Amino acid sequence: AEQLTEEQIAEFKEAFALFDKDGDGTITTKELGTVMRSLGQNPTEAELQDMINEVDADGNGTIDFPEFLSLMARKMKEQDSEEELIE
Ligand SMILES: C[As](C)(=O)[O-]
Ligand SMILES: [Pb+2]
Ligand SMILES: [Pb+2]
Ligand SMILES: [Pb+2]
Ligand SMILES: [Pb+2]
Ligand SMILES: [Pb+2]
Ligand SMILES: [Pb+2]
Image 1 (spheres, protein in one colour):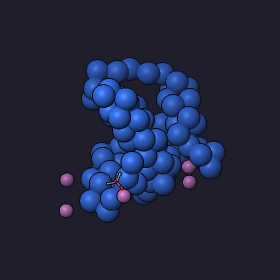
Image 2 (tube, protein in one colour):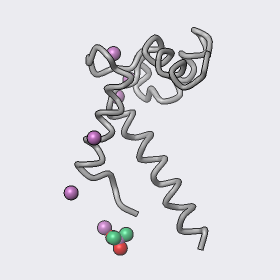
Image 3 (cartoon, helix red, strand yellow):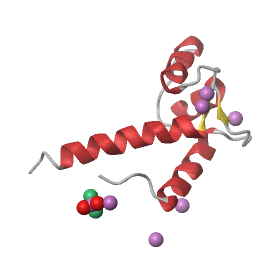
């Protein structure tokens, strides 16, 4: 019911940085693969691109912070809708 706050955005930027190791404002398939493997995953090279294209709104090949935030916003809107239904 509420849009992302400055503090939430700041926390999301830290999360973004966990993927974007070189801090160039993007998340590549390579960086994505590194994160997936750290969670017990092992997707394929081309399989990583599919996940990227799914979040990559401007279709430039990588994920930028705005698209990352958009996803987080959609997720929050989802949990908020459910938590308001659980009643
Ligand atoms: C969802 As509200 C805090 O604007 O009532
Ligand atoms: Pb409000
Ligand atoms: Pb505060
Ligand atoms: Pb923090
Ligand atoms: Pb990067
Ligand atoms: Pb963008
Ligand atoms: Pb992009």
